[PDB]
Length: 154
Length: 154
Ligand SMILES: Nc1ncnc2c1ncn2[C@@H]1O[C@H](COP(=O)(O)OP(=O)(O)OC[C@H]2O[C@H](O)[C@H](O)[C@@H]2O)[C@@H](O)[C@H]1O
Ligand SMILES: Nc1ncnc2c1ncn2[C@@H]1O[C@H](COP(=O)(O)OP(=O)(O)OC[C@H]2O[C@H](O)[C@H](O)[C@@H]2O)[C@@H](O)[C@H]1O
Ligand SMILES: [Mn+2]
Ligand SMILES: [Mn+2]
Image (cartoon, rainbow over all chains, first blue to last red; front, side, top):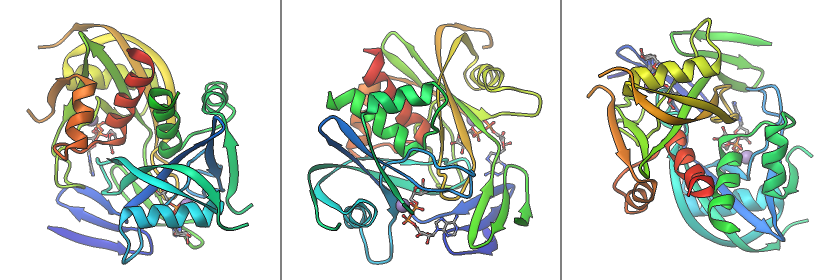
């Protein structure tokens, strides 16, 4: 039995007995490789005070399913379209939030549309090296993209 | 300039202009392989109403650094100790929270201590197959462990 403390724009804060629970819209993220570069994006994220390396990601809006949201945010954030394949999903931090991320692969990318969101094409090997040297932070989606590449796309 | 709406046990809810921000303690997670099985754990997570496949994880408590927290939660959740190596970190969902997870590898595991938290040794290949068939959900830490294994531990 959830009692609500806050109903907001992209989250609700609830108590469920002793548990603090943040309800959040589901998200999507897209892994895309071109000429050995992965498609990352960076934007200022006020929650962390910096711009981590992410892959294109967004929230699922009313009416959409994950595939449609993935197509939309790839086009909105990078101007690209591709052939999308569902990979897997994960709960970002299920000890306090229900946010679930659905991750897709994009292939055969084409420009459909010509630095709020900065597009950062970067070899995943270099992203991993920059992170190990302390030069860039990852979001979960960025790290999942780099690990998925090393596991399956070489 | 953050104004606080809620100060709680494992999170704070703040507004920073138009942004809803959840402050949260940093976390650790430990990837451990033994005889081709990865060390997963499962527990009921009221935020999601189910028990996703995770790897041993916990919050960093006052006084600790990530390595020490990782040692602690491995022992508390599974009764094991090992030789720990830092791998990488990630922000779980930097569009709304500052929670950061530090991920370690554990090797040479030994039992130091003899189903609140269920220990689930499982080959990562099988965890990935069960997830693809809809039989289990992943946390970010579980998915990162499975992807890291496939990338680097075969
Ligand atoms: N929603 C909550 N509200 C209030 N207290 C809680 C909650 N969840 C746990 N506790 C209390 O907080 C103590 C912390 O339990 P520890 O093992 O260090 O952490 P973890 O495994 O939960 O979270 C580790 C990560 O894994 C997941 O991705 C999480 O989202 C984190 O990112 C618990 O004993 C409870 O007393
Ligand atoms: N903290 C916030 N509070 C209020 N509104 C916000 C906030 N952040 C963004 N908006 C608004 O919400 C709209 C959503 O922007 P979209 O691209 O679909 O999502 P995403 O990239 O932010 O989040 C995608 C995932 O990546 C990260 O891991 C996140 O944590 C998510 O898990 C924005 O245009 C803003 O209008
Ligand atoms: Mn976005
Ligand atoms: Mn735990």
